[PDB]
Image (tube, rainbow, N blue to C red; front, side, top):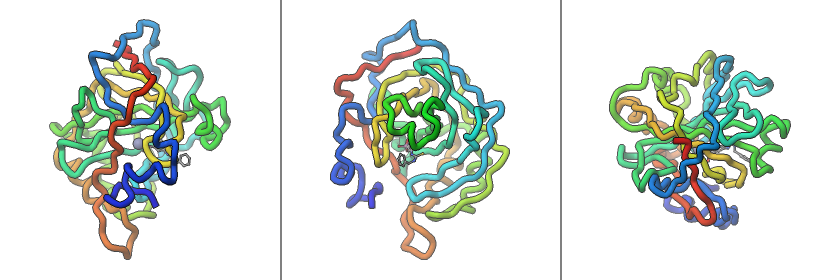
Length: 256
Ligand SMILES: O[B-]1(O)OCc2ccc(NC(=S)NCc3ccccc3)cc21
Ligand SMILES: [Zn+2]
């Protein structure tokens, strides 16, 4: 199936998922000088106080930290959003080198990784129904640059040994995602899609201007993960990012 290899990577996805060449695909390059400041954009409201993390899983494409989304515990609202969006999971995209790894780029600059906090619109009842709507998901994207260590990321880094291969999972309770946020909530926003198959155009993207800093040791551990399952040839889970797609008929708005 699809992946990030030379034979099944992003350039091949359109064959099984034609929407790959759609009108509102993600990620995109954020041209800071062309983005339009929108004074009507409200401040973001991130309420992760009652977040309930459950487990961490290696799904063969990335590792996801999953949350209990049966109630409005951890939610995103405000900004360009209308309604309440519940946090269901977060994961990252990273490179084989510090010079690449992010999906979105800023003035063509690639960051070492990119965190995606995925939320779905409660007006649609469940995640499955939400992905079928143009405003079904809200994904908060946060860039990672290599520098000082990120304390709030260490609990994640330390459990990676227990989910090295595809299909592995581990309990991951009491993890506070607030420890992954930068100081500033200034952001760019635009309508887009999932960056992985099925590439549905159901995402309101909110990308934070301020990256978080992580250490070389922390990102290096991400690169020790495996795309393959136990008992199969080892394939290092690196460069699980889709390159920037055509902006087409869209305008990126800035909150600042
Ligand atoms: O492209 B991304 O890595 O970035 C942002 C993002 C958000 C959600 C996902 N997909 C999830 S939670 N399930 C897969 C699925 C989705 C829709 C239908 C079937 C199956 C992947 C990504
Ligand atoms: Zn993602």
